[PDB]
């Protein structure tokens, strides 16, 4: 089984790794019958997107925001606007 | 999809942005049958709630409670202009 | 609609406001369900049971309230006011205000 | 209803109160399934377990007490089990 | 019933106890169908995953990561790779 985010990210289609090593600057959450958007100080902006796994990821990004912990890497779907998160590495 | 709260707000009917840039002064929660009511207010008196003008509603309530507990600044709210307290459609924390 | 705990409290039957401005001194939890909180003055309150108070009290909201009260206890944050039902002993919590 | 842990503990068959006033020294948990346990131990060797949603809640409370170093004041436990099974907890 | 992680680990088949006494250096979570994969790593390269929801264990590891609390021991199926976690002990 894949051992890290780079290996995991290769298993998906239309994805790439963003290496950020930064805390989340802005956290946005909206009712969508919830969409979650995060941005970083350099302006990189990502959205979340299944029920259960998506709630866990939304909780993780929310907690990261409130605690100011560093996001190391994201694996994202690059055919989406903003790009959609497949995996997260905190380190 | 829009990547900021201003444009997201524009996609709902009868909503507006309030720019706050301050921490929640009071957080109130009450039993209301199948759901809890959750009301927040700020130092200038602006009062807002979570209520549809399910799971996502719960998530919003938890975000506002966490914001209250931690004293984190609320940057913006997109709210519906229905009731006072106005219902929250979106939140931005920065 | 009501916009604060005082206005909300008047919508229920058999309630009162309790003015606290204190952190929770004692948190008690039992699985045989019951959550009880107490403050330095001896003021003691319980969380309601699902299906009580004309169905104003139901399982999922109560779980959320239990979460809030436990967080308040652990973090030492002040409870400003409670809206409490007086038809139970200890009085049971309808609403919580944190400030 | 009971107003404290002593009153509630008196309501059940084969329970007893242990007074601790100590922080949790060790927290152990296994995966959901038939072998799922949460086990807590204190400095003096005293060890307890949590044997639906009330069960979830109590496990969460113990885990948070460990993470934070909050003192456990009292436990109401069934002592027809080893480790004794927690019926109620008092934090103070 | 078991009273500690070693006794708990012996209720599983082909498990071992990996002693660590270290904080988690990296936390990775990823979307799969029906559940998220969760992978943790330590500074020495030791890498573990949660799999047989297993939501409680996932919550515990994430909280350990966020708070920097030490993971004392893991009971793992050490035939899996990365090894899958059956139980965790938190101690300092």
Image (tube, coloured by chain):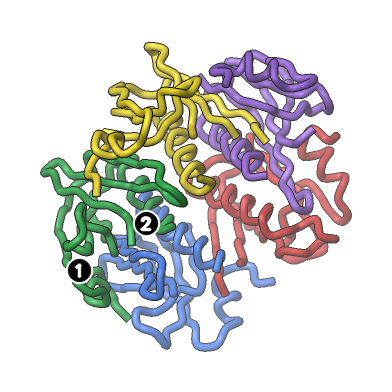
Chain colours: A yellow, B purple, C red, D blue, E green
Q: Is residue A61 left or right of residue C79?
A: left
**Do circles 1 and 2 both sit on a common chain?**
yes
Residue D87 appears in the rendering:
yes
C92 or B39: nearer the viewer? B39
Residue B91, above or below C4: above
* x, y percent for residue C37: 60, 57
- Return the residue found at the far front: A13
Element marked by disc 2: helix
Residue at 43% from the left image edge and 71% from the top image edge: D50
Q: Residues within 10 Å of mark 2 (few under 14, many from 20)?
A: many
Which element carries disc 1, helix, strand or loop? strand
- Residue B16 on image: x %, y %: 73, 16
On the image, the x and y values in percent for residue C41 come to 62, 53
Horizontal side of residue D15 vs D2, given as left or right? left
Q: Judge from the rendering whether residue D20 lies leftward or rightward of residue A82; answer left or right.
A: left
Spatial CA span between label 1 and label 2: 17 Å
The label shown at residue E57 is 2
The first of marks 1 and 2 along the sequence is 1
Q: What residue is at 49 percent from the left and 27 percent from the top?
A: A47
């Amino acid at each position: 089984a894949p051992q890290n985010i780079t290996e995991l990210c290769s298993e998906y289609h239309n994805t790439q790794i963003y290496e950020l090593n930064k805390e989340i600057k802005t956290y946005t959450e909206s009712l969508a019958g919830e969409m979650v958007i995060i941005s970083f100080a350099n302006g990189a902006t990502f959205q979340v997107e299944q029920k259960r796994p998506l709630e866990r990821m939304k909780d993780t990004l929310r907690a990261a925001y409130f605690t100011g912990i560093k996001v190391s890497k994201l694996c994202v779907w690059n055919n989406k606007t903003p790009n959609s998160i497949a995996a997260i590495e905190l380190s």
